[PDB]
Image (spheres, coloured by chain):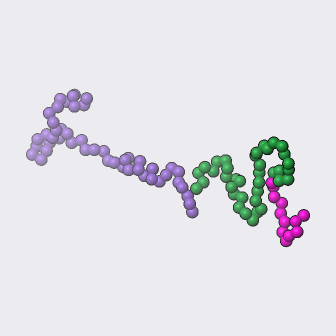
Chain colours: A green, B purple
Amino acid sequence: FPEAAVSRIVVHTRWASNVDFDRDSSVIMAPPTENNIHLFKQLLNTETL
Amino acid sequence: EQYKARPGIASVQRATESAEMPMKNNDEGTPDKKGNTKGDLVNEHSEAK
């Protein structure tokens, strides 16, 4: 486990894998100290300035 | 705040200006300052056509 003052859990599909064919549809998040708003505005946020 | 209004303010304002226009004055066939009727010598029915 990481040796640090604070540790957190993040989702990262196939972050440690060795596949032969890539499905090429993955979900990656940054640590909560960085903005992740771009993941929730991919479908119908075509009017968000 | 960065808000882009839909419908746009400019587009709506332009349309309402045209509807603001009062109707034209139809003074044909009425007398004048001296008492002569105002208009041209065209047949009553042919004028409508």
Residue A43 picture location, percent across and down? 67, 47
Q: Quadrant of residue B42?
A: top left
Residue lying farthest to the bottom in this orientation:
A5
Residue lying farthest to the right in this orientation:
A1
Q: In which quarter of the image is residue A31?
A: bottom right
Residue B21 picture location, percent across and down? 34, 48
Q: Is the magenta stretch mostly helix, strand or loop?
A: loop
Q: Is residue A41 left or right of residue B16?
A: right
Residue lying farthest to the left in this orientation:
B34
Q: Nearer the viewer, residue A47 or A25?
A: A25
Residue B19 picture location, percent across and down? 38, 47
Q: Which of B25 and B12 is in front in this view?
A: B12
Which residue shows up at 83% across the image and 63% down it?
A8
Give the total of numbered labels: 0
Task: Locate the N terminus of chain B and report the quarter of the image it occupies.
Answer: bottom right
Q: Nearer the viewer, residue B26 or B4?
A: B4
Answer whether residue A9 is magenta in the image. Answer: yes
Q: Nearer the viewer, residue A20 or B24?
A: A20
Answer whether residue B25 is magenta in the image. Answer: no
Which residue shows up at 17% across the image and 29% down it?
B43
Q: What stretch is highlighted in magenta?
A: A1-12
Q: Is residue B27 left or right of residue B16?
A: left
Q: In this view, does B39 lie to the left or right of B49?
A: left
Answer above or below: position of A22 versus B5: above
Q: In which quarter of the image is residue B49?
A: top left
Which residue shows up at 19% across the image and 30% down it?
B44
Answer above or below: position of A14 versus A2: above
Which residue shows up at 80% across the image and 54% down it?
A12
Residue A32 picture location, percent across and down? 76, 63
